[PDB]
């Protein structure tokens, strides 16, 4: 029983951008009304209730590598 | 019983952009009204209830590699 | 019993863009009204209830490679 | 029973950006009204209730590598 | 029973940015009203209730590597 | 030359209303964009240019009598 | 030359209202953008340029009598 | 030449209101942007330029009589 | 030449209100941006430029009589 | 030449109000930005430039009589 785990990974992620100019985020907010009474969350819940919200994201490169290696022997 | 796991991966993701000009995000917000009473979430729930929301995303390159390697021996 | 897993992968994703000009996202928001009483979510639910929402996405290259390698021995 | 875990990983994430110009985030806030009575959270809950909020994120490069290696022997 | 855990990891994350110019975050705050009575949180809860909040983040490079190596022998 | 101006005016305006119930004025505002360069107004001009506006008027009786008496001798 | 100006005016304006209940004026504001360069107003001009505005008027009776008496002898 | 100016005016304005209940004026403000360069106003100008504004008026009776008597002898 | 100016004026303005209840004026302010360079006002100008403003007026009776009597002999 | 100016004026303004209850004026202020360079005002100008301002007026009776009597002999 011989298991050889040898992932040869050569990877490059490259973003080339000269200049990012005028980014204008001007939003006139509104109205959010939320009515509830009983909220039950047990395990690993991500919940946003009644949000007015503004996200301006300007990453120079925004590159993301996700690598998962799982080996299980039963 | 011999298992040879040898993924030779050579990968390149390349975005070339000179300049990003005028990005204008001006939204006049409105009205969101949500009525509930009983909310039950058990396991691994992602829930957005009653949101007014504004996302401006300007990544220079926006490149994303997702690589999953799973080996299971039963 | 010999299993040789050798995926030779040479892949390139290339986006070349000189300049991105005027992107104008101006939306006049409206009205969203949602009435419920009892919401039950058990496992791995993604749910958006009562959203008014504005997404401006301007990636320089927007390239995404998804690679899944699964080997199972029973 | 021999398990050889040898992931040779050579990876580079590169963002090149000359200059980031005018980023203007001016949002006129609105009104968020949330009414509840009983909230029960047991295990590992992330919950935002009644937020008006403004996030301006301008990372020079915004590169993120996530690598998970899991080996389990039963 | 021989387990060889030898992950050879060579990784570099590089952000090159000349200059970051005018970042202007001027948000006119609004009104958040939240009414509840009974809140029960047992284990590992992260909860934000009734926040008006302003985050300006300008990291020179914003690079984050997350590496988890887990080996369990039962 | 005899001019007898004797307007005998007996007038009554009567509004009887028991109760005015739920008046709900919730309008999600939109977007108004107006471009001009040269505006010339000489005498007695009433002008509204580029307005987004909300008027809720609930008078208990809203009764209006307009009486003009003009006598001119040339 | 005899001018007898004798307007006998008996006038009553009557509003009877028991109770005025729930008046709710909640408007989510929007966006008004007005561009001009040269504005010339000489005599008796009433001008509103670029307004976002909210008027809630709840008079108990709202009764208005306008009476103009003009006599001119040339 | 005899001018008899004798306006017998008997006038009553009456508003009867028992109680005025819940008046709720909650407006989420928006954004007003006005660009001009040269503004010339000579005589008796009333001008509002670039206003975001909220007026809540709840007079118990709101009764207004306007009476103008003009006599001119040339 | 005999001018008899005898305006017999008997006028009563009456507002009867038992009680004025909950008046709630909660407005989430927004953003007003006004750009000009040269402003010239000569005679009797009333001008509001770049105002964000909140007026709550609750007069018990709000009754206003305006009476103008003008006699001119040329 | 006989001018008899005898305005017999009997006028009463009456506001009766039992009690004025909860008046709540809570406004979340915003942002006002005004740019100008040269302002010229000659005669009798009333001008408000760049104001954020909050007026709560609760007069018990708010009654105002304006009476102007002008007689001119040329």
Image (cartoon, coloured by chain):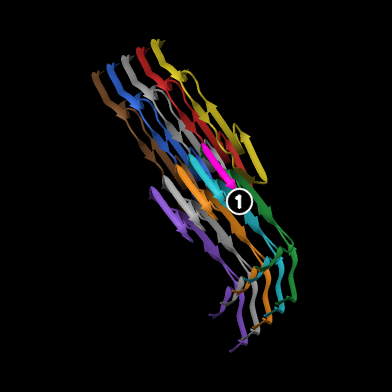
Chain colours: A orange, C purple, D cyan, E green, F brown, G blue, I red, J yellow
> Against A48, is G59 above or below?
above
Q: Label the magenta part by its dominant secondary structure.
A: strand
> Residue at point 42% right, 17% down?
J17
Q: Which residue is mark 1?
A: D54
> Against F10, is C36 above or below?
below
> Against C63, is G72 above or below?
above
Q: Is residue J24 magenta?
A: no
Instruction: For the N terminus of chain C, give its image quadrant.
Output: bottom right
Left or right: residue I31 versus residue F54 is right
Query: x, y (%) of residue E53?
Result: 62, 46
Q: I13 or E19, which is in the foreground?
A: E19
Q: What stretch of residues is rendered in magenta? A: E37-43
Q: Is residue I40 visible?
A: yes
Left or right: residue J24 versus residue A59 is left
> Residue at point 54% right, 40% down?
E39
Q: J11 or A19, which is in the foreground?
A: A19
Q: Is residue I3 visible?
A: no
Query: x, y (%) of residue C7?
Result: 60, 86
Q: G17 or D53, which is in the foreground?
A: D53
């Amino acid at each position: 029983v011989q298991i050889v785990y040898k992932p040869v990974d050569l990877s490059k992620v490259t973003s080339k951008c000269g200049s990012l100019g005028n980014i204008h985020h001007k939003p006139g907010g509104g109205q959010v009304e939320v009515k509830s009474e009983k909220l039950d969350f047990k395990d690993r819940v991500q919940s946003k209730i009644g949000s007015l919200d503004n996200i301006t994201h300007v990453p120079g490169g925004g590159n993301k590598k996700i690598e998962t290696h799982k080996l299980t022997f039963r």
